Image 1 (tube, each protein chain N blue to C red):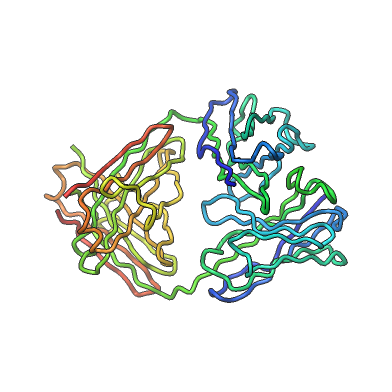
Image 2: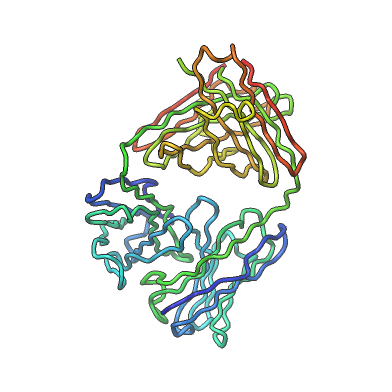
Length: 217
Length: 207
């Protein structure tokens, strides 16, 4: 059966290069247009480039023009993406794909076979301790803890040294200004706080950080 | 041109799902559709508007009208819950739609609970200001978040998390608006608007 196997993904600095490979078997490789398509964390499919079956025509997304080049070695049944001048925003899973339509029909009939994906992660971030801020409002009450600007993973967050685990929501990290930001909320009865103490405890071992932040009105 | 599609479509098992793609010159092209499940490669389900490749279940079909193309799943199954992307091309590029998550309903719908927090005085000492909009207990698990400052839509400085599953099996997410301390002081009203199942839940702060 028809198959594409990718390799060459990695972790590099902005400004550097990578070569992705996509090794094809189970079809007449030189009879099909081939594409690269990428997918950033939680985002949609984003076309990158196409090379025609015979290698005569290459086209690129505006986002990569001048930086990435696509090629194929039909003698080795392999497709390449030469990624130069990498940027943080190039971070994504990269797929190769084969078109269903052979030869001149390749744009018309969809992409029928896809690689498994190879991950490219581009960052210049150094170890950075989080800043830990209180979240408080201007029957029940919702308080929280903002863990802003740490790198790398991991970080841990607990409430009252783990003693308070009910009514807690700890949200996924997101990348913001090339560092990670996380938050957690805790919902309690309004007669409990501020009469009783609520403290967020944040640990980030890379930066030797252990912070306790008491939530005040 | 850009291809757009609804971020979310939801149906109960057995119902027919309809997912529509639209774009300025889409009617001059053939549209195809991909199914993608989490951590998996896309799968071509429909091409040339209405044709199924071998192995794709008969319940997947497609149609087109005007500058739109529609994927239809007749008798939806729990296994069909996935992201669906349309794809065509324009004068110089291949174009993908932004994706629709099809949720096959396994529990009652639930609107989001929204909470908006101001920047802390501690953070403002650093010349920076972050507003935090937390969003919990929603199902299906797709929201769109829009921020306004003094009634004006914000386009910059925002990040929203991917939705994630809670212990009760509903979803949560959070959104952040980062401003300079000086921008924070210049404006009086701030709003986090969360759209879910065609209805918007708003929370605001005002000085």
